Image: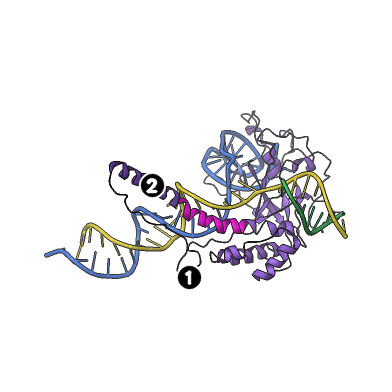
Chain colours: A purple, B yellow, C blue, D green
DNA sequence: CTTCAGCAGCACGTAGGGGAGAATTGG
RNA sequence: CUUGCUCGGUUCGCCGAGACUCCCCUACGUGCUGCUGAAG
DNA sequence: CCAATTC
């Protein structure tokens, strides 16, 4: 299940004011700082509407509006498994420690010597009762079935300065027959360069790639990022994820690249089939500005 | 003005916790 | 094989060779440096 | 149609 990466193009507001991220942050902050008894007291986080509703009242965690059971479940199981996992880490060493102590004691008993004393344990709780190596908050925003990427159809999605695509039409191809371009137009290969061009099948880089306009010791062309990007989203494929009043729109060109180098798909493929190769629950990075996808089992 | 000694990391590892849905269903 | 990333050739028009299991977190070595004390 | 249920 390899991962595939995708860049963002627009969003309503920064992914920090989202109810999902705020609720996950509050839940984590509450759970990580629990005592080894309060963990078992508040560990009956439910799976239904009523159980997950009454847990928030019992534990008092602020709720910013988020109520999705599928979206409130993915940010409680992870938090409690991380809490339990730190204890699992501090108790993993003690298993081999006890095994080694038992082996040494058995060897001494066989030799006749009395068993040697060993350290009891290295627990994870200090005088305050809380946990020593308290975990850090995960900024990842995990998606779910109810909110899955779909083709950006402007029928209901809001008005953006973007283009539109047919989910049924096959995906466009990257300027076939490169050596037919008028002079003075983007992508033009001068005549001296046409001899000794690559004949093997490889990635077809676009004119407005960032690798062709970048600072380099022997590159005298001037970098114009403002135009290099403003003329780069015209040929973009837009996929949209939507939780509430939020409308992340992405670029399904990373997905298109991903499907073409693991022996998966060819130029004859519609948008619906493109993201039908991927799991419907991507992971979002609020600070880096990237979305991560995963293939299916096939 | 040389050896140490218990701490911190702009950076590199490592080591070990956690994680990365969808099909059947109900107002 | 349209975005993204790495390394390069160029008349600067874009050309070539690549990698693609990723993220988060708490610890912990290393020179670097800082903070003290022994040593003629 | 689209939030909630088990797996």
User: Where does residue C1 sit, x and y in percent of width and height?
Assistant: 70, 37
Q: Quadrant of the C terminus of chain A?
A: top right
Image height of A98 relative to A49, above or below: above
Whole-Å distance between the Cαs marked 1 and 2? 32 Å
* Relative horizontal placement of residue A268, taking residue A32 as reference (left or right): right
SS under mark 2: helix
Pointer 1 residue: A128
Q: How many marks?
A: 2
Report the residue at 51% width, 63% height from top.
A134
Q: Are the residues tagged 1 and 2 within 8 Å (C-beta)? A: no
Residue at 62% x, 62% y is: A43
Question: Is A79 included in the stretch rendered in magenta?
Answer: yes
Range covered by the magenta-colored residues:
A78-93
For the point 61% across and 59% down, the residue is A79
Camera-nearest residue between A230 and B21: B21
Of residues C30 and C29, the one drawn nearer to the viewer in this rendering: C29
Residue located beneath label 2 in the image? A102
Residue C27 falls in which quadrant of the image?
bottom left
At a point 67% along the width and 47% down the height, the residue shown is: A293
């Amino acid at each position: 299940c390899p991962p595939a990466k995708v860049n963002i193009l627009a969003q309503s507001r920064p992914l920090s004011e989202w109810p999902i991220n705020l609720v996950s942050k509050g839940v984590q902050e509450y759970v990580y700082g629990l005592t080894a008894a309060e963990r078992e007291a508040n560990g009956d986080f439910g799976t239904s509407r009523k159980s997950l509703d009454r847990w928030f009242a019992r534990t008092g965690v602020p709720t910013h509006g988020y109520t999705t059971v599928q979206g409130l479940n993915l940010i409680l199981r992870h938090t409690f498994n991380r809490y339990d996992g730190v204890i699992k880490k501090v108790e993993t060493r003690n298993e081999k420690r006890r095994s080694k102590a038992t082996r040494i004691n058995v060897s001494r008993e066989a030799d006749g010597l009395p068993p040697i004393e060993a350290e009891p344990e290295e627990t994870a709780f200090g005088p305050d009762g809380k946990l020593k190596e308290r975990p850090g908050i995960n900024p990842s925003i995990y998606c779910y079935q109810q909110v899955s990427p779909v083709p950006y159809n402007p029928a209901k999605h809001p008005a953006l300065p973007f283009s539109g695509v047919d989910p049924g039409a096959p995906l466009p191809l990257g300027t076939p027959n490169r050596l037919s371009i008028p002079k003075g137009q983007p992508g033009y290969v001068p005549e001296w360069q046409r001899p000794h061009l690559s004949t093997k099948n490889k990635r077809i880089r676009k004119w407005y790639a960032r690798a062709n306009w970048r600072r380099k010791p022997g590159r005298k062309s001037v970098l114009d990022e403002a135009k290099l990007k403003e003329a780069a989203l015209k040929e973009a494929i837009p996929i949209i994820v939507t939780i509430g009043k939020d409308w992340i729109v992405m670029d399904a060109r990373g997905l298109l690249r991903a499907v073409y180098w693991r022996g998966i798909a060819k130029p004859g493929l519609s948008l619906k089939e493109l993201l039908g190769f991927f799991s419907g629950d991507p992971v979002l990075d609020p600070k880096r500005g990237i979305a991560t996808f995963t293939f299916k089992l096939g």
